[PDB]
Image 1 (tube, rainbow, N blue to C red):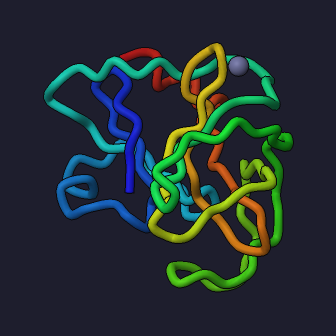
Image 2: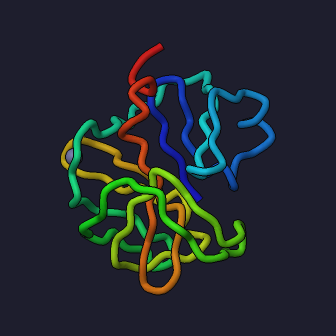
Length: 140
Ligand SMILES: [Zn+2]
């Protein structure tokens, strides 16, 4: 589990979105596994605006933050998980690391702020849903 709180936005994995998230929906995209809902309270997370490929992510299944190199946000074939079939997922970045379903929502951060959240796992890779192209999170 986990979310990003930026401005009056809450960013979660689409597959973990709550009724309240859907009842306050701003934007959602199944192909990215992202959903954004509106918040009453100001969030303080800063979204990275950069093309970093090194950062640190939180892995709830190990109670650890791991430094990782990660790939460029891309359209990748993801094998079936407990929450999605085998499919193509867009705006996805991979690293070598541990990721189990419960780890979805863990933050990947770089020197510029939050890069994205854990979205995929398996076969020794961790996949992150990028948010750095969502420039509107910074405004409105
Ligand atoms: Zn960065």
